[PDB]
Length: 81
Ligand SMILES: [Ca+2]
Ligand SMILES: [Ca+2]
Image 1 (cartoon, rainbow, N blue to C red):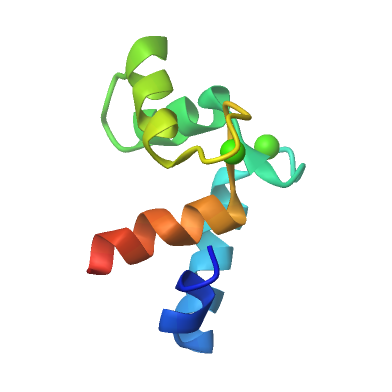
Image 2 (image 1 turned 60 degrees about the vertical axis):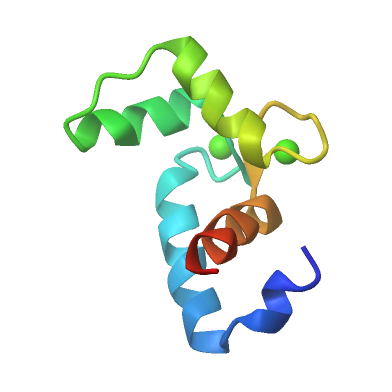
């Protein structure tokens, strides 16, 4: 979470915040399975709660069951590497 904000350009960070901000429908600061499922559906997919659970669990370092912004950058940086 330290190296992600390092790796990246301020430009990339900005576009990532925008996206995050799109996913975080209630503006509370983290993405829940409900939020995740809602957007996935917009993208044609049909995920189950399990599936959603498994996706967040890969990037969830604090065990909150939700994805915050820092966990969100890591999932994209990890994506770029
Ligand atoms: Ca939220
Ligand atoms: Ca979390």
